[PDB]
Image (cartoon, helix red, strand yellow):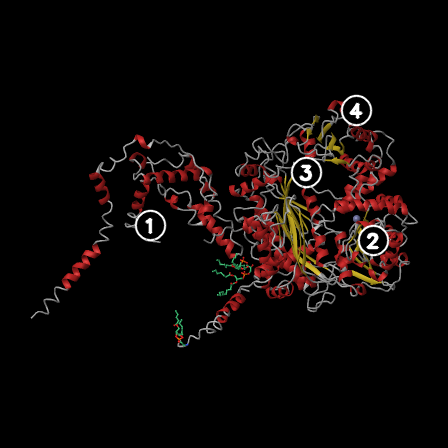
Amino acid sequence: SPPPPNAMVYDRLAEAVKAKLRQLENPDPRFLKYGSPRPTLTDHTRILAAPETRVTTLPNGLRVATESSLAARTATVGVWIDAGSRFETEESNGTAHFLEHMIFKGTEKRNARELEEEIENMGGHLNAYTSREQTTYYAKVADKDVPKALDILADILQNSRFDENRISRERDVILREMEEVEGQTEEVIFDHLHATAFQYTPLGRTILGPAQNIKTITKDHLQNYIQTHYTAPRMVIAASGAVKHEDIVEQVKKLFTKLSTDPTTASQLVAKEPAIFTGSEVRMLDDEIPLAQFAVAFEGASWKDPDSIALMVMQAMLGSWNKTAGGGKHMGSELAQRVGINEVAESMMAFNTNYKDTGLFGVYAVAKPDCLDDLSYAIMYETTKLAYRVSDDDVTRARNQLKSSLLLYIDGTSPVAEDIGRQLLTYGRRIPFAELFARIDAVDASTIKRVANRFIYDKDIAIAAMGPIQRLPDYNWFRRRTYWNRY
Amino acid sequence: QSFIDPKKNWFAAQHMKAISKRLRRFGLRYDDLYDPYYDLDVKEALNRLPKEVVDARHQRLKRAMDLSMKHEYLPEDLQAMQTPFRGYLQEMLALVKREKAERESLGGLPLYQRTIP
Amino acid sequence: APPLDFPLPGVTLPSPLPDHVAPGKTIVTTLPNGIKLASETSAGPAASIGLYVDCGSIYETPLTFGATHLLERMAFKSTRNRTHFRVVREVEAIGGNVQASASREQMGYTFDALKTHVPEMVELLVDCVRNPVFLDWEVNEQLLKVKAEVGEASKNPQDLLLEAIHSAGYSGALANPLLASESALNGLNGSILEEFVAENYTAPRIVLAASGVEHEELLSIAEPLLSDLPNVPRPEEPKSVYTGGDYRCHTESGHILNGQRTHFALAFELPGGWHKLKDAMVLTVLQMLLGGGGSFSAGGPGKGMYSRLYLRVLNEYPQFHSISAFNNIYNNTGIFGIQVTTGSDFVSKAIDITVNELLAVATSGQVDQVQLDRAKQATKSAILMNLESRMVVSEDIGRQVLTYGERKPVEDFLKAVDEVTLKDIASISQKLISSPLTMASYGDVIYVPNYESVSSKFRS
Amino acid sequence: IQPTDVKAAAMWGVAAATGGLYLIQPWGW
Amino acid sequence: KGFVPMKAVTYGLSPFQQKIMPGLWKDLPTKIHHKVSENWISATLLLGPLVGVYSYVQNYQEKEKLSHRY
Ligand SMILES: [Zn+2]
């Protein structure tokens, strides 16, 4: 008279959990042959072949670089300039961004409607973006319109006209472009972080400028900016796709003949006004906003610094977690396991910015106002641990991830050409794929601790925060936790 | 090993019916003695089980805490219907412990930790 | 180590590629059970492998509603051979990226890493699709995130509408919803997903497609792991009919504040979608010909500034904030329409400004031959620039050997855009308005017209 | 790493002997 | 900390409807036999090694006392 093991609902719901678990016990050894969860370091030399990059310096100082792939049917060609927001004077602070929007509107040969129609009749595109140190103008076309595309970029950079009916109608496009980027809150955190870390230096200003500068800017200002900065040693013509190097050189030798001739380089302008880091903070409390956002940053490395590659391996150790991600509680990074297991944030991200003389290294996070204590403990605990205790599987995995993310990003004709043009401006050369992989795996566990002791250990920080941030710890709490009084 | 199997040994087939006798009088199973406060892994094995299986465990435990306050036993009709040693917990608890030995050999923080009292 | 302006001394450099690398041709292989492996080489250092299944949201009987929006969230998880902790750690060990997506007719699972890791990339992809266990504590923690995102979907009013031009408008399979409601998330568990997959994931419906892999490598790896799936007869394809329909939902009761949106749209139908090849390329040209945008986006020359719906609607009617065409082609049926937002006090004539434009292209005479050539150039380049990515290339070999049984060369796509004249733009757009008008709306619904007030302005 | 943890941690054993005879001079032992 | 969701039905009487004292001297012969036929190996393990050691000491001390007498 014991009940049989199918008679009660709770007894036969328990023989069905034991049968679900007996199919997790006999693994198939032919599905386990190549994959391994332990990271190793491997050699990628057989697959790293590429076409040749050919650089040619014209006698005025202009450089022309190409990577030809003659089996394609498209192309990308553009101009990279060594100028930006840093090289202005606070009475001309929005000028390099205003000049970007006023350069597709001029020309004595083709007006605004004619220029807009020549591009769309071909089926092409024409873009532009500004930053604090670099400007770009480039075009995506088909392979038979490359001489027409290069004809437009030379004429809109040399012979543009800026009339008053067009200037004043751009003052209301930009004054309404300001108002939308006052509501993205990741570009607002990172813009107050630059103004407090690099205060009283030219690197602390914003790109769009103050709103009083925009309603004052007139053509003269636009014309002295384009005669002081857009000069031949500070410009790179880069092309990629179905192009030929010797045919592009003869086109630019007769099209670019009339640009200015000032012999001031960019390095004479960085050296007479350098950038200096200051430990400080900004806090904007509102309490009607539901989520809080903040960033904490150390000073980092410049472009040509040999320690720059180790601050990119370290950024891949801190990692990234989001609430929609499929990794979940199982990620490699230990900062992402702390955030993920306890649910103490909405999202977390580590950043690393390089400049000509300085840089920034840190973490950005979004969270609910009752989680800010346990989140700030976990961020500071794992950054300071890089100066003390570094595992060997942590750096092998973070080297395999940085090798893969730098090359999976170069996919198509336009990622290739912005790789050529941006690297000739920062390093003076394009680094081949086999040297770049050789500098990455020369970063072992002892290299991590030595760069962490130079940049992180017992150093000043900069914080910018916004929202319901009354429970975020103060500056002395953060400054104290850059070292460990234990050991 | 070789001194615990009751169908080969004689002194393990008398230790077996001594615990079987004492469990029937309160109507308990051997897995009801596993406390989620003793071992934090037992707390996790019970959250992965169906709601109807955990509810029958909470009702066997309440019937037995009522019999020992009153100083009595189950009546002998109900004592012949009892199955001690019919388990519901050992296979799910071995799986939780096997997943924890894998997360430690490979690096990785523990999923739940004990509070320090 | 030297500064990064100076080269590092002791490293071997591979010898470079020539300036003209000859492109490879797609190789297709059919196994005895019915599975099709398809491969193509490339000139980058990276590979991209995908697995595409014929199943989708039209195979959902009323016992399994919502069971493909959940299979997209249960994608790379615990199998019979690997736990969910070992799957996450194996993908991060080689620096890969993994992803899944679900449609009304197609499921797809992708992987991409460097070309060194091709045998690893294949056997993890086959094991995660062929052998999923569905454990209840993993399914229940994914259901609780779908339940907290059906809490609000009202912040994307162009997939709210695009799903509402689909239920109102069809009857059978194509009216099954993609992202499901609250009650069908309460009848779903780990055994519904388990036998939905054992029935609908069969060998005649699976295609493996690689981009940057040699065809004899992909057969040394993937053939001993897929050859023993059984050969079963495929099922009969689910059927539906295009009726007309109206739909409207006055918005959720907090939406209107001081300002008020209006989101409406119209639609039509045209019997074949991809097995009648000639007709679909005419409509992609007609999409770039009509075009339009939201127009407060500030890009540059290039994306729809000189379209019909741009310089004949938003360039002189400033009360519009968005107008654009939309095509949703499927296999043997199709949908073409136009989505509009406007103001609440400027609404009913915005239906009238809209409809004329669909009447203007039905006329022979109103369109230029300088407007047709622009839409014919902007369409051949959009196909050619998009095929530069290795991920779009692998996705093309997948969804073309699921529709035609073979990959069509891109020369046959540029050949048949050339042949389109000014009268194919008129005839197919006259075969477009011979079908009932599907209408949908959202926001302040009170100020809009009704079905027969608009549907008799076309034909029938 | 983990060696440097103990290669630190055994000199606080000895910072504590510079300290353990600092006030008491435990003599006979 | 203290919540187990439950489902049960309980009935209860009032204190002033029952007999409080007489349930002590109820079946004391039956109560005694239950306690001593279930706790007789726990008293053979508590008094056993004490009665046997006291017998050894009293025998040792009664043979070195009769060996010192002349
Ligand atoms: Zn702008």
Q: Which subunit holds the residue at mark 2?
A: A
- Considering depth in this image, is B56 or C99 the residue closer to the camera? B56
Do labels 2 and 1 touch, CB within 8 Å? no
Which residue in the structure is indicated by mark 4? C457
Q: Which subunit holds the residue at mark 1?
A: B
State the CA–CA distance, disc 3 to disc 1.
65 Å
- Considering depth in this image, is A395 or C278 the residue closer to the camera? A395
Question: Element type at marker 2?
Answer: helix
Q: Mark 3 and mark 4, same subunit? A: yes
Whether residue A420 is visible here, answered yes or no, is yes
Q: Residues within 10 Å of mark 3 (few under 14, many from 20)?
A: few
Residue type indicated by callout 4:
Lys
Closer to the chain start, of discs 3 and 4, is 3
State the CA–CA distance, disc 1 to disc 4.
89 Å
State the CA–CA distance, disc 3 to disc 2.
36 Å
Q: Which picture quadrant has residue C311?
A: top right
Which residue in the structure is indicated by mark 1? B5
Tell us which disc is closer to us: 2 or 1.
2
Tell us which disc is closer to us: 2 or 4.
2
Could you tell me residue C325's position as x and y percent?
Answer: 77, 35
Question: Element type at marker 1?
Answer: loop
